Image (tube, rainbow, N blue to C red):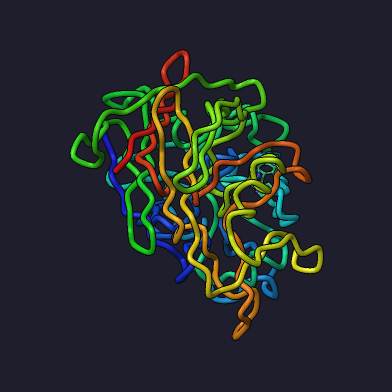
Amino acid sequence: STGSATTTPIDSLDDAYITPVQIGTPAQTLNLDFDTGSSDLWVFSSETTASEVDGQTIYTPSKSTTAKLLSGATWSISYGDGSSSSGDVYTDTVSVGGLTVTGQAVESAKKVSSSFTEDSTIDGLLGLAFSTLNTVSPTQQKTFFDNAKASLDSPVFTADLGYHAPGTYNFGFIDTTAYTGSITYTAVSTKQGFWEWTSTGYAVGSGTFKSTSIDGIADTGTTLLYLPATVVSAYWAQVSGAKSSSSVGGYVFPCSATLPSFTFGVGSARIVIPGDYIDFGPISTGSSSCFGGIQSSAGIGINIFGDVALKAAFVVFNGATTPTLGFASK
Ligand SMILES: O=C(c1ccc(-c2ccco2)nc1O)N(Cc1ccccn1)C1CC1
């Protein structure tokens, strides 16, 4: 089997991407944020505190003939931006782009933090990291990808995120028309439950490439590119007037600037992020100070290849017995 679904930026900055997902019988279509940095599939639901729902589409398990309460199971998650959600769990049929999993754990939110309520465009998350991070208790649950893997033609999914445009998540096959050149594959460590890999270095604009190992995660659920402070300083030093602002919470730059590209290494290959991908626009409406798309990871404890980086590539998440990641230009 295979699946193929279009993923769409939620706003004009590509702050996140939503992909439609069919849950239950008859189908209830919810727009989920596919997140390779987490491992819970959770949704706004008929159980969500009513004051915490503001325009999202909800899953109502009582209207699904295939929903079954997973008795006793609860879940609770916190994300690196401080947001969180929690609730109970049902199993139900879940389809993505024509690929169906029966008995998928669908984690129904009873509570969501303010950031979720305030984002009417995201109806939930679909976790695609390793199942060892799944928060369900007392019996940890598998991700949609783990449940589907055995049926898939090839035990892979691919992320092809667009810049200010739709893109695609595919399951079970590699679309050889979707990228240029070859795919370079690199080793993955699952020890922290993430798609954790080691970049071979970086370049700023037309500058010389610096060979240096940068350990970090491929995280579709994170907007920006978070890298060591030395790297980020070198990038922003090339932008006249850029500075790190404690009041804003990162690097800002004059909106009048033209940003340089940023290249990261994947083995001997190179992925170039165009400068325009690094512009996240005015810090507040009407400001001429713009927010940078490359920020320091020093506060986080891990480097994160988020959407800014991933949208410059066609990315293979290879869930073979020994997982690997593949990157190609496109
Ligand atoms: O939001 C998280 C994050 C945190 C915790 C968990 C997790 C799974 C299960 C329990 O906790 N999963 C994440 O997905 N980021 C992305 C991030 C962090 C900080 C700033 C920006 N982006 C990843 C790094 C851990």
Residue 248, visible in the rendered structure: yes
Front one among 141 and 14: 14
Q: Residue at x 32, y 39 (%)?
A: 329
Q: Residue at x 50, y 50 (%)?
A: 307
The residue most toward the left is 177
Report x, y in % for residue 206: 44, 45
Q: Residue at x 63, y 82 (%)?
A: 287
Front one among 55 and 264: 264
Report x, y in % for residue 158: 36, 37
Please state if 90 lies on the left or on the right of 95 as rendered. Answer: right
Q: Residue at x 36, y 28 (%)?
A: 156
40 to 274, vertically: above or below: above
Report x, y in % for residue 123: 52, 62
Front one among 82 and 151: 82
The image quarter containing residue 150 is top left
Quadrant (top left/top right/bottom left/bottom right) for the N terminus: top left
160 to 184, vertically: above or below: below
41 to 58, vertically: above or below: above
Quadrant (top left/top right/bottom left/bottom right) for the C terminus: top left
* Quadrant assignment for ligand 1: top right
The residue most toward the top is 321
Residue 60, visible in the rendered structure: no
